[PDB]
Image 1 (cartoon, rainbow over the protein chains, first blue to last red):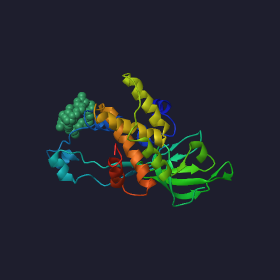
Image 2: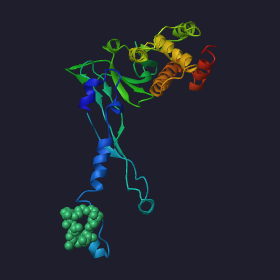
Image 3: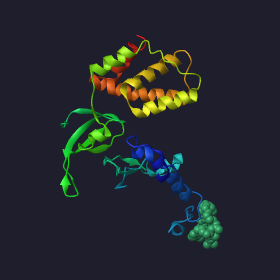
Image 4: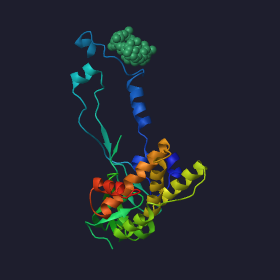
Length: 50
Length: 49
Length: 159
Ligand SMILES: C/C(=C\[C@H](C)CCCCC(=O)O)[C@@H]1O[C@@H]2C=C[C@@H]1OC(=O)\C=C/C=C\C=C\[C@H]1O[C@@H]3C[C@H]1O[C@@H](/C=C/C[C@H]1O[C@H](C[C@H](O)[C@H]1C)[C@@H](O)[C@@H](O)/C=C/CC/C=C/C2)[C@@H]3C
């Protein structure tokens, strides 16, 4: 955002033209999949779920 | 700026997501706002995050 | 100048509508902060009328500019050499300039071009985008429909 802020011309931009949410959703999906802390719910019985 | 993250409903129910291998998601809506110090305007979009 | 409920063309975003003229506070004073929503970007733009002339906001030009660009087309014979990167830079700077007549002349040049030659992919992207904003300005210049303005194009474009 700060990078393209200077490269973009005035009176022609909008937050839709400024913001890339692709790295944000990539960070969310990169945490929920393929982390250490995200885990398959070990659920052979409800006590192991709990 | 950035202001007021809010949500929509879920995209799909629980077992439907579990069957179709979709993540049980919900959209993020954010009242984003851009302001120029040069002349001064608000640019109050609603960015889907 | 501007009253609530009037259509008004705001560059580069084009035509938009005023919702109110708020006098909100900064530095003690309260100025002509007109809140204005647009149709494309779906955002509300607080504009002060003290620098509406700075940003160059525009009441919608009608049949004067319409017949102006309609006088320009159907023999829009321009010379530009095969320096087509220079051509694209020139019309991109023109497109940033946001003049209705020049933008219309260049997209009718692009119509004349792809009628024979065929534009590039991003060239056609720029073509369709400028057709979109120019047609929105036209369809609120006559205060009418998008399909009406497109039929207007088809019946004037070398016609
Ligand atoms: C060593 C380790 C996990 C091992 C695979 C199992 C943990 C020890 C289980 C035990 O002996 O009691 C650590 O796991 C992570 C962080 C560091 C380590 O990463 C590590 O070094 C190893 C893996 C880190 C992330 C793995 C992600 C994915 O790999 C698969 C899918 C995703 O997560 C894994 C899920 C494992 C659940 C386990 O659950 C255990 C039983 C089984 O061993 C497993 C079913 C249950 O005892 C449960 O109560 C205990 C859960 C562990 C608590 C939090 C662990 C986070 C599954 C194997």
